Amino acid sequence: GVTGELRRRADGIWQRILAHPFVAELYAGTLPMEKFKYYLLQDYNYLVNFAKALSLAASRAPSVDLMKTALELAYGTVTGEMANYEALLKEVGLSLRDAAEAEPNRVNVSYMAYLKSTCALEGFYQCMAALLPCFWSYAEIAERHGGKLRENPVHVYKKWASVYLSPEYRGLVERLRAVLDSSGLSAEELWPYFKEASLYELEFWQAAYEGH
Amino acid sequence: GVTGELRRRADGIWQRILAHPFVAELYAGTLPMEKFKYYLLQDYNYLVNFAKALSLAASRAPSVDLMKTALELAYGTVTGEMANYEALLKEVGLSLRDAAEAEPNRVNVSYMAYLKSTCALEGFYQCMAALLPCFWSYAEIAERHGGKLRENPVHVYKKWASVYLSPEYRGLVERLRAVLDSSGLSAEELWPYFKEASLYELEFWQAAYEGH
Amino acid sequence: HHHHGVTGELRRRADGIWQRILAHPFVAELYAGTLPMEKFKYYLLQDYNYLVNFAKALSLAASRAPSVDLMKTALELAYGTVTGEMANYEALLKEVGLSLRDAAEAEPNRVNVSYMAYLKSTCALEGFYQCMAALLPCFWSYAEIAERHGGKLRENPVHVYKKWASVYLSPEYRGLVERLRAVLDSSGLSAEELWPYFKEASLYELEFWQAAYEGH
Amino acid sequence: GVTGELRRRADGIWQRILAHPFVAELYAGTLPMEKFKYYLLQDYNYLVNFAKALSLAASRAPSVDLMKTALELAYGTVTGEMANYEALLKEVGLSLRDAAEAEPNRVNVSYMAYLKSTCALEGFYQCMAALLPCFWSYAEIAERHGGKLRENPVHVYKKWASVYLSPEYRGLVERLRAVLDSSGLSAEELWPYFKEASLYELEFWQAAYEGH
C-alpha cells in the first residue's frame, strides 16, 4: 500500500499537524472565534483553487473512470462543499462577498500555487499524491480529536468537524488511497509531492493560528 | 444577442448540418445500424475528451461561478449524455471496452485536438464559444427532426434522440448561451471559434455517414 | 548522439503511411522541378502557421521535460524554429516575391489548423517522450523525402526549389533527426505505447502535402 | 506607463528589497562568502524553473513577435546565464553538479510554484507581470548599490553584479517594460501578479541571508 508508506515517511510532519494548537483548540472548543473567522476567510481561496487543481487533474487522467473520479470531486467542491462553506459563513456572521474580498495569506498563495502548478505540468497519479494530504489529514484529525467534540460548546465548530467524521467523507478518502495504490508507481517516486503538500498543510494551520 | 449573431453567420454551415443525410436518416429510422454503431464508437471517446475540454476550461475561469458552470456543464455531460451512451452500446451489442479500443477517425482526432488545444491556451469565453456548437446544434437537430421520431421503428434510435428533446438538455444549452451573451465580448471577436466548431460538427457527421 | 530501438519500430509500423508520403506527387514534382510555382507559393504561405505553432508545441514540450538537458534540447529547437528556420523561411519567400506579412495574413487550411491543434493539444497535456513521438515525423520525414528524391535536384532548374531542399540534405539536418531518435530511443518507453502519437502526426504529414498539392 | 504604476504601488515592498542587508553587503563586499555560496546553490532551482515559466509564457503569446521574446529569454536563461552561473560557481569552488543536488528552500519552491502556476494557467501579459519583478529589481538593485563595487575587493561579487549594470541587461528590462506598457491592460488588473512576485523576491533575499 504505497499510500501507507507515503503516510509513514510523512509521520514526522503529520504528527506535528495532528498535535497543532489551532486544530486542538477547534475540536475542544477553546479556539477564539476571531482565529476561526480568519481561517474561514482563507478557506474560500483554498477551496476555489483546490477545485481548479482537481479539474486540471481530471483533464488528463489515464482512464475515463479516473477522470469521472476527479471531475465529480471537482464538481463536489464548488457546489457540495461550497454550500456547506456558505452556511458556516452565515452562522458566524460573514458572507461569500467578505470571503471573496478576503486576502489570501502567504502559505495560502504558495500552497495553491504549488497544487495548480503540479496538476498542470506533472503526471496524473503524481498530482493525486499531491492532493492526498488535504483529504486524508483532515480525516485523521477528526479521528484523533473527534472525541473532544462532545464537550465542545461552540455549535459552529461542531458543525465544521462533522463533515470529516462522516462516512461519506471517509469513504472519499478510501477511494483516493485506492487510486494511488492501484496505479503501479513506486512510493519513492511519489513522496516529493505528498511531502510538500503535507508540509504546506502544516504551514497552513500555523498561519490561521497566528492570524498571519 | 451575441450568441444569436454567431448562429446567424453560421447558418450556412448549420443549415448543411441540419439537412445532413446521417441526421435525417437517424431521426426518420432509415439509418443503417452499421453506420449508427460506427458513430457510437467514435462518440464515447469524443465525449471523453469533451469532458476533459470542459475541465481545462473550468480550471481557468475568471470567476468562481463560471468555474461552477463549466464544471456542471462538464459533469452534466458525464451524467446526462455519457450514461445514455453506455446504455446505447449494450442495446446495440457493443461494450465500453469495444468503444475504448475503437480507433478515432481523422475528423474525430482533429476536432477533439482542436477543442483541447483551444481550452488549454485561449481565453475562457473563447473556449466556451468553441464548445457551444456541440451542445446547441444537437438541440436544434432534435428540434427539426424531432417529429419524425413517431414513425421511427428503431428503439435504439428513439432512445438516442430523447436526450436532445429533453428540457434538461435544452436547459443545459441555455446556460452556455447566457455565459457567452453576458460575457462582454463581440460576436466578431468570438466567431472564428464558433465557426471552426460548427465546421467540425458538419465534418464529423459526414465522417460518420461514410464509415471513415 | 545516435539511434537504435523504438524509433525504428515506429517507422516500420508507419511504413504504409510513410511510403504514401515519400511517393507523393507534390514532393516528387518539387525535387524534380516540375511542381507549378503557384503550388509551391501556396505551400510556403501555409508554412507560416505550421512553423509558428510547431514552435509553441516545442515550448509546451520543454515546460515539462523529465530532465534539464532534455529541457535545454526542447527549448533550443523552439528558439531555432523562430530564429534560424524563420530566417530561411523569410529568405525563401523573398525569392518567390512574397513577404512575411503575406504569410502572416495567409489563411491556414483545415489540415494545417487540425494538425497544429493536434501537436499543441498533445504537447500541452501528454508526456514528454509522447510529445516527441508526435513531433518526430515532421523532422524525420523531410530528411527521408530528401534522401529519396535528392538525386533529382541535379537536373532541377528551379533555384528556389533547390534552395528549399538543401536544408534537408545537409549533414546538420540529418544529425538533428538522429539526436531526436536518440532521445526517444533512450526513453525506455515501448513502441506500442508511443505509436498513436507517431501515427497521427505521420497521417497529418501525408494530408498536409496533399492539401498543398490540391490548393486547399 | 502601466509598469510605472505597478512600480509605485509596489514601492513599499521594493524599497525593503533595495535596502536589504544581503544585497547591501554583497555589492559592498561585506557579505560572508558562505551566504553567497548558499545563494548561488539556491539559484539553480530559480534559474531552471524560471526557464520553464518563460516557456509556458511563450506557448501562449498573443503575437508571434511576443512568442520570440519569451523563447529567446527562456533559451537565454538555459544557455548564456547558465554558462555565467557555472563560471560563477567555479570561482567559488562549487560545480553545477553541486547546484543541481542543492535542496531548494521553501521560498524558492513556493516562488517557482507561483510563476509556473501563473504561467501555465493565466494570460500572457499577466505572466509577464509575474516575471517582470525578477528582471527589473536586479537592475534597480545594481543601480542603487553599483557605486559600492569600486571599493568591493571580492572579484566573484563584482563579476556577479556586472551583468545587472551592463547596458545589455538594462535594455532587456526596457523591452520587457515596453511589452507591458503597450499591452493595453490596466495596472490595477495587472498588479496582483507584479505584487506577489515582488513579495517572493523579498522573501528570496531574506532566505539566502538566513541560510534557511
Image (spheres, coloured by chain):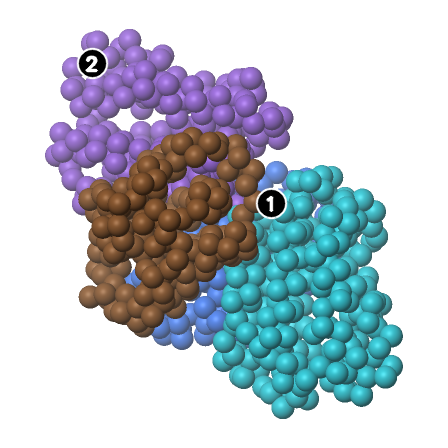
Chain colours: A purple, B brown, C cyan, D blue
Whether residue B23 appears in this view of the structure is yes
Q: What's the mark number on residue C127?
A: 1
Whether residue B121 appears in this view of the structure is no
Q: Secondary structure at mark 2?
A: loop
Front residue (pair A208, A128): A128
Q: Position of residue C71 (x, y in %)?
A: 65, 52
Instruction: Identify the residue shown where x is 66% and y is 88%.
Output: C96
Task: Specify whether D57 is left or right of D28.
Answer: left
- Is B72 situated above or below D129? above
Q: Quadrant of residue A212?
A: top left
Front residue (pair C148, A183): C148
Q: Which residue is mark 2?
A: A152
Instruction: Identify the residue shown where x is 54% and y is 22%.
Output: A181
Q: Secondary structure at mark 1?
A: loop
Q: Amino acid at mark 2?
A: Asn
Q: Residues within 10 Å of mark 2 (few under 14, many from 20)?
A: some
